[PDB]
Every structure is written in C-alpha cells, then in structure tokens.
Picture (cartoon, rainbow, N blue to C red):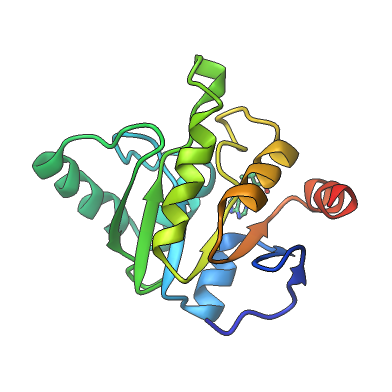
Length: 165
Ligand SMILES: CC(C)[C@H](CO)Nc1ncnc2[nH]ccc12
C-alpha cells in the first residue's frame, strides 16, 4: 500500500493519473478493485487490462468461481486472488446504464468498497458501462467511507475530475 503522487480530494478519496495496472505492479496493494460484469468475463476496459496483466490467470480463476457460485448481481461483488497485482481482487459490478440498468445501483456497487480499509480502484460504470465519470466520482465520494486510491488513465478525464472536485 505504498501509494505515491496522489491528490487528496476528500478525507478518504485520493486520485492519480495512471493506468490502474501500473499502479498495482508498483504498490502490490492489499486490494485492487476490478470493474467487472456479472459473469466475470474480462474482455475489455479495466477488466481486460487487469486480466491481461495476470496472463489470463484472473480469467481462469473467475470461470471457476462462476461454475461453483453462479453470476454476481448488479451492485454486488466477490473477493478472488489478486495474483501478481495485489493480495486480493475485489470484483465489483456497476450498472451498465446503456443497457437500462438503474443508476441507483452505482451506490450499491461502491458500498462494497467499505468492507476493505484500503483499496486501489477505477471509476465504476464509467467505461463502456456508459455512466458519466464525474457523476461516478460524486457517488464514490458520497458512499465510500474507507480509504480509496483512484487511478484514472485518460489525462483529459483526470483533468476534468480534478477541476470539478
Ligand atoms: C474507467 C475509465 C473512465 C478510465 C479512463 O482512463 N479507464 C481506466 N482507468 C484506469 N486504468 C485503466 N487501465 C485501463 C483502462 C483504465
């Protein structure tokens, strides 16, 4: 958990312009959050990037979790291995608002972070799930009570988030 170069936005939310994968390799945090879907199929966005950095070990473990437990619910989570990136990976499902899933579930999704004292995380529902990323940061700030270190790779978005905050 040796985080460097973050800006403190609130008492417990920090932000940095970085690829979450590079932050995980540098810090090896206790928990890295994945922006997952309900079947834990890590095909693109943050999920695809984290799985590729484990050389598909995350996907083989996720497929076994689904075989034994069934899919997660939107707003839900599960804790699996963090492989080479972290001690644990917290897979969290935000709503895919472009497919009509309710934006109210973005609060439920960020509530999962409160089970861990310190997390390295992306913005939920803010990639291909279609939610406005500045709205996602507002829900994060209003819901997470533990220490969250957010990594946002796109500099244009990072600058807009810092300016809005
Ligand atoms: C979620 C989305 C707004 C954001 C935009 O840069 N994506 C990411 N954020 C952080 N590390 C990442 N690695 C691969 C993608 C990615």
